[PDB]
Image (cartoon, rainbow, N blue to C red; front, side, top):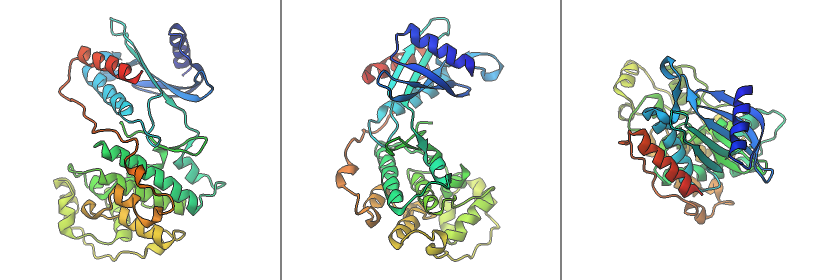
Length: 341
């Protein structure tokens, strides 16, 4: 904690960095985060990647093949997008030192809050105008990721960030059970970008309700909570998007439940808003509304501009996973820091 801040201050000083480390934010295996300020007063989160105690002994991240590759992929993904709705790299710098003393520094803008905090603050009014605006930006961030072949896979209010200016940014796309699409709950290996559309629909209903929509605690009771709202899916559709183990879990599951009226599930949502939520929360991803069709839905009529579908997009993300050599990866970090500057 107090050592992480002291280590970072000294290292950034030796570097003549434009930063001032103000306070300690968080610490875990693989890196420590400190809240600092850039040379212009803008608050930043400074992540320092150095060591870990993996398998019992102290390992240098950038020196071990697997861990180095994991961090290189997180970095390459952050550096791939340049879009207002996707959290980007503010800065990146690498300190290579021969006897496994390699350090990596990651700088991102420190956001004011996240959507989970906003939803749960009873003193905050989340109006239908605020919901439409937030949802428009959430879906544009997903559209941008999906256009580059990237699936978030763990979208939830905690990773939907709000700037002081209330700008929406999605993070943690480069790495609760309550936001998982039926195909992820059923451990289907063939999941697609449509899992994100399910999470987004859960987030949308939650902003109206001020409470998560499907608050299950087990594989069966989570699926039951979903089916109670969406109605019993055809068994043929369940077998198509479940793992063999999940099919066997659901083997003797008797289900003959009608869909509920959506007005009862999300009482404060108007009919146009409900129509979109019901389309995002299709149990079967083959019938689930795509990001483009959700963005074109009359719910966003007052905000929508077709230019939002194509501006600031990135090309398809490619990561060559055949890479294994740490020295080959170190060159990619140097190349990633080069293309950055």
